[PDB]
Image 1 (cartoon, helix red, strand yellow):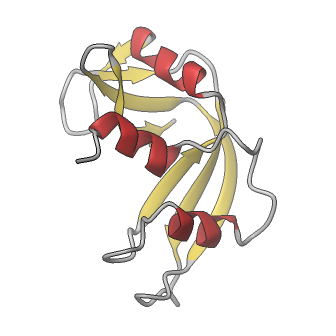
Image 2 (image 1 turned 60 degrees about the vertical axis):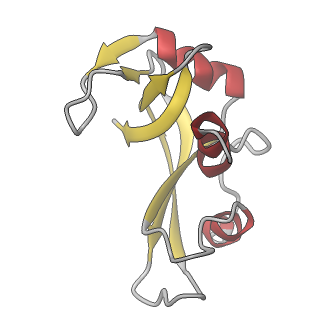
Length: 124
């Protein structure tokens, strides 16, 4: 089955664009990445950086995750991110999202060997 590392890439990485280019970005990406297959996922964040730069966060500032776990890491630098939030008109299977561009530090949970991101915790 898909590994947690692979799932992170699928759900969160978009190295192909520098930023969201239109209001439809979230709608398009949430669908293409299979995030809306079973239900509309309510919130999601895409990171517009190289995968290596995001993997490197696992060796950056150790911080407690929102749930209290201690395997979270905060990036030293801000990153280009897109926030996707379900709109009032969203109705499965026609999931609808608002796209918001931001530049923020990211917080991820890391696991394994190699030690890589497996969960997106927050943007600060």
